[PDB]
Image (cartoon, rainbow, N blue to C red; front, side, top):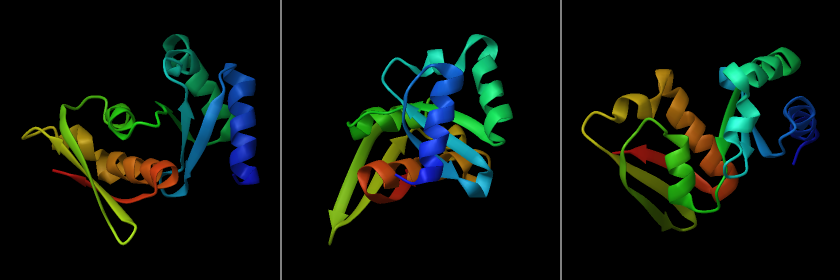
Length: 138
């Protein structure tokens, strides 16, 4: 939407040759999360993640790549890769949507990410693409 995000999307394709649906800026963690089409994540990363390294050089921020999906469960699984997600649950009331992910006894480790880093990525992405304003790992 913004011009900044518009710039990021343009440089992403310029370096990788892959089209980014969106670029979720995360100033707090000096990070940029690029959303790409299904099956495209490997092309965007490159051999030895060389393209990730060039994007960091190019945009001066940390770079992350996630495959987008209009299906909440799908993108949720993409958002928490090294995790066993049993069930996802979305509750809405007065237009307030909250997602509750059910991960096994101790999958809560990778789920949260060092310093919420991971679950914040979930919140940011689900907030921008699904109107979800609350995420909960249970």
